[PDB]
Amino acid sequence: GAMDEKFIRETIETRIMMEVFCLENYFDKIAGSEELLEIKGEIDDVAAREIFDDSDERLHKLFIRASGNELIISLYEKIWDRIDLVRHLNERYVVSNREHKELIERIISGDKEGAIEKLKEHLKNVEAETIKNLYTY
Amino acid sequence: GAMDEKFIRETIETRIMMEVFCLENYFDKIAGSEELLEIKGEIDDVAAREIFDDSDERLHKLFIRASGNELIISLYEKIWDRIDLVRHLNERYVVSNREHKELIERIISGDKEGAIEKLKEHLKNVEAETIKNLYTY
Image (cartoon, rainbow over all chains, first blue to last red; front, side, top):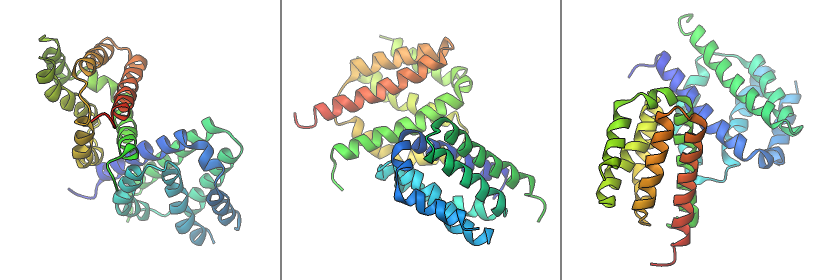
């Protein structure tokens, strides 16, 4: 197949399926993790680009890893190069970092409903902006 | 890794993640599909064993297929042999067929909330019974 709108949308939908499931069902484990606080610290040291690569992959992989489900973890690893291709299609470092900062604060503060909403929003926003700029190369 | 409780639980949790996501988000497509009715017809023509093998794989693959997301479809295909191994660990034909019949009727009748509940119940019930019998071979 081609690297087209459908490819992009399928990738983001798959991420929503897996990441939201894990955040919803493992919320407390995620909220209490030392990894989350280290990522938060990385973001709070504002270099948007340098903050981004690292923090973004760590945060989204943390949601998945918190399940402890090696099959889920392995499926996410299998699709990671495709996830990463899609990430690199469009640079959105400042705004993604802000969305992450706010997502993390919703998690830590115990706002589970709001955290799930912010993760969905993040992924849909990335999707829309990637599609919006697919012909602006 | 071993074929153990963790392996089984991971499999079922992965199915809940993927199947419930697709049922929830593609409910009307699933409800309006000819395949769903052909499966219903198979289950209602009545031979629990013969009804099961074909119907079970078709029904759960239909939920996934209705997404039209080739990545989700391909990930479910990748895990299918593992899903199928787990299915074959414990024979529940009559009761799984009954759960499927009722799940399908919830879907057809427009009871989306009840259909999602029945799917989750089915998979958790399969899980529990497989674990309960893991040392009765």
